[PDB]
Image: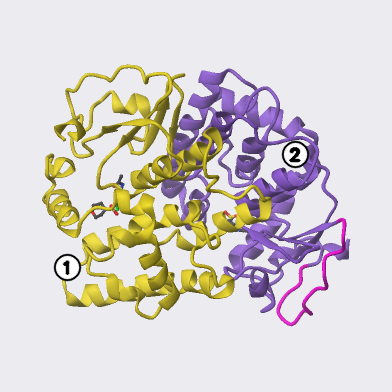
Chain colours: A purple, B yellow
Amino acid sequence: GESARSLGKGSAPPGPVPEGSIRIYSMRFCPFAERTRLVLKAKGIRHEVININLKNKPEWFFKKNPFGLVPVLENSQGQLIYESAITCEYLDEAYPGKKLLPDDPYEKACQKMILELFSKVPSLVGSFIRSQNKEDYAGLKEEFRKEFTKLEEVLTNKKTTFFGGNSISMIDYLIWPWFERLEAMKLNECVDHTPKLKLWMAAMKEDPTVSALLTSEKDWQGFLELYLQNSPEACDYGL
Amino acid sequence: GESARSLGKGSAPPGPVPEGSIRIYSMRFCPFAERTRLVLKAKGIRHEVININLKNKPEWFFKKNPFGLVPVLENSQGQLIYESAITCEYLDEAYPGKKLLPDDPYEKACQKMILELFSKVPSLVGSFIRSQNKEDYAGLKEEFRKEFTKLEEVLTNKKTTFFGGNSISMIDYLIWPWFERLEAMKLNECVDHTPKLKLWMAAMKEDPTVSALLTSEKDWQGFLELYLQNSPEACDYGL
Ligand SMILES: *CC(=O)Nc1ccc(Cl)c(S(=O)(=O)N2CCOCC2)c1
Ligand SMILES: *CC(=O)Nc1ccc(Cl)c(S(=O)(=O)N2CCOCC2)c1
């Protein structure tokens, strides 16, 4: 729908969040905000979405988050929560349904330590934007392969389908958005020496939550070409 | 005591952690490891300490933490936990006594969002090491002042003694080590336009846990001059 169109500079500040719902301030192609949206879907949390034009931001958005970044949660009480991992943790704790983080303190620390193993991967997206030719591409693929070997080791040791066990859990949703984008970045071959990680991607794409939120390669390319041309229209690609 | 002397290259791998105790692999001047040690003291957790010579590390230490970094917790069951904030969270959850993180999901997310406001400050220690003259020092003081204004705003809004309320809590211990070191780095004047932050430092130094772990300026300078000369003896300064 046009209902998903972003609010940008000059938009009216939105009204209060209705009792019984939580609001996410998101952007449809942002992988950090996708984390929060995977959790909202996986736990069956009633919510509304406000997309932000990250090239043409409303000044009122800095009242939601002084950093000016998505995702942000806002509840009916007016409380604001930001930073992707903090939003996810908050939702798992505040709402009923599937516990995505273990109750056991050690197993919960393990999920966070895996998140730490992953922590170099997002900054590699800036690396991808600065890659201009085949030489830069070869070096970019090597950087992805050395982070991916760290994740392969965890699956080798656990011999589980997923990073937190045989059931999908929080850590899987927290890293998935970057794996979702590998095909579109032409980095799919970075998982070819990481066989368990490659099977984990196939298992993720079968998860009902993942499948319900997955964006096509054509849609992510439309976004990236406008985001790279510096277009105020990038966030609204397709609408 | 000489009992605190670091284990370095060639040391024997240590034995199992006794039932009823947890072990921290630490270094006496590392502010990340100090986080974990403030939590261990604040909750009254029985523990042993193994100091690591971070200039002359035992090869067995990479079996504790593949990153080779302190702090690491090891319990009687053989479980290993690393990354400073993860160790602290784990201890607050796994042990009885003073809850340092709130039970309320929102108030817990607030502490983590403040931690995020602080997240540039530790990398400013590398900035300090690279500062060579009065011009670099002036620029370094400005960088500290812009991060400190973000923390001042939180105290202005809450009008509480501490970052999590009127009682000291986890977030205060998580940021204190860097404030402890400001005098020794000659950055004490970076809090002079942040009056609540300056009163918060005076309140911290009165906390029994903080006071019990505080290192003198003379001791931190002895460490830093050896750490800067690249000395294998830096971590054992004073012993
Ligand atoms: C919400 C959002 O998109 N945040 C964000 C911040 C930095 C980076 Cl690099 C990204 S990205 O990695 O999705 N990136 C892909 C290449 O250019 C567009 C953004 C996202
Ligand atoms: C455990 C440890 O000390 N980690 C660590 C990592 C990086 C930096 Cl920069 C520090 S520091 O900021 O304490 N630093 C002070 C100046 O030089 C010595 C180390 C600590």
Q: Is residue B41 magenta?
A: no
Above or below B176: residue A194: above
The magenta region covers A6-20
Residue at screen point 17% across, 23% down: B10
Q: Mark 2 or mark 1: which is in front?
A: 1
Above or below B161: residue A138: above
Q: Which residue is mark 1?
A: B132
Residue at screen point 50% across, 53% down: B169
> Helix, strand, or loop for circle 1?
loop
The answer to whether the residue labelled 2 contacts the one labelled 1, judged by CB atoms less than 8 Å apart, is no
Chain of the residue under label 2 = A
Residue at screen point 25% across, 34% down: B51
Q: Label 2 vs label 1: CA separation? A: 51 Å
> Helix, strand, or loop for circle 2?
helix
Residue B234, position as x, y percentages in the image: 15, 44
Q: Nearer the viewer, residue A65 or B130?
A: A65
Residue A52 falls in image quadrant: bottom right
Residue A1, position as x, y percentages in the image: 88, 60
Q: Is residue A14 magenta?
A: yes
Q: Nearer the viewer, residue B209 or A236?
A: B209
Q: Which residue is mark 2?
A: A210
Q: What secondary structure do most residues of the magenta stretch adopt?
A: loop
Q: Quadrant of the N terminus of chain B?
A: top left
**What's the mark number on residue A206?**
none
